[PDB]
Picture 1 (cartoon, one colour):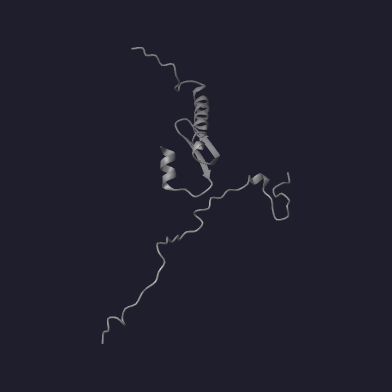
Picture 2 (cartoon, each protein chain N blue to C red):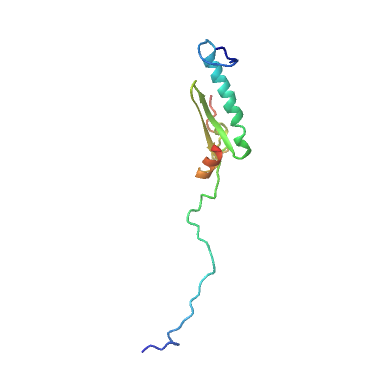
Length: 72
Length: 49
């Protein structure tokens, strides 16, 4: 079989850092959409291959409903 | 001896209030950018470089 796969995976000198870049751009782009409904200051972002995490701080104390709505 | 009328009273109260225990949860609070943070003397702190 031969399937069209014009995308990214491992097995290359470039894949790792470039995927990190793309995830960084992705999360920076997504995280400027939560801003339509919340006020926060992006304190830190980290991206490493098969995972990524971003921390963010609020004007007040956290509740369950903000977590739920942010998740949705 | 139980006198029904003389034993009767009228009790007063407030109508339909709501008691809020915590008091600062309604406050949302924020800090100026800590690089440009200033003290009592109107002179910046963390300025020497």
